[PDB]
Image (cartoon, rainbow, N blue to C red; front, side, top):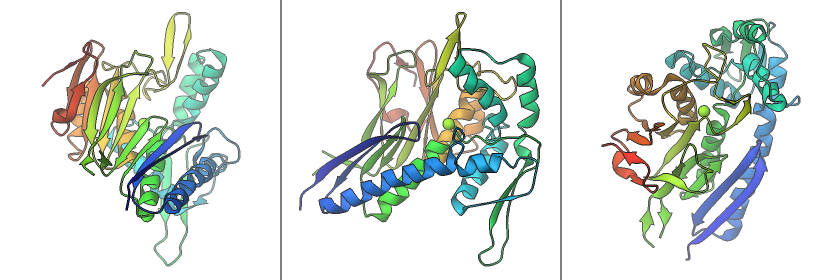
Length: 330
Ligand SMILES: [Mg+2]
């Protein structure tokens, strides 16, 4: 039986999602799996989206400062994980930052920075500790979420792609696929090994933080690993000479000022990589290193504004510089 390579890509969840698969299974089986991948991505846009009126998350937010709302097991589990990372990161990653994000989101659409007072007011409504998750223990008991703080709003944008990537990996596995590369707007999951009959690690590129992105600065070889990168270039606007990027510091309510240009997190679960990449950007290098010691099975790669690159022990030997302006410190 012969190995075939397949790819499919669509615009969905606000970005380009592409899955590449190598498989010796009948083509019709791979096609079936890919059909389901992209159906899942469509259905989940309608669960998780913070910027759509129809979604289950928007309906949940419409009940801030009221009674508990029943949610499916999957959303509950995602929120649990998000609150865990909010606690561990000291609020650097915060899934209850919707009131602030919403102000900045109109800012982007308008090319305008939000009013100082409006932001300070929004920051009174971002206490993730007031998100109460409860699940009864009895057979078939429902899962519920209560937003106890008035006008608090969830925004799962900084963890949602990792959640979906992990869900897609579970689906691929359920379809007896064990070799794939999932790319959801740049959040990568490398499932298994690729083919050359020889089996090889997937080679994932990391962009120059200040480059068009067309070519990678560095490449890392990985198996069964997510690679998620946070940088100021993912989304920003400019007004009066200043760039305002999308990664908000929850202490200031403004885009984070940090000592790294990008951080890339390598983890067994993309959900974890996504949350950590966001926290780490906000935290900066030294505080990140401290946080990451609490997650032994995770690795990281930092690109500094002076083009120095530092990578943790788990992956440093798997990093290759492609753009010689960058230096890998060992
Ligand atoms: Mg993130």
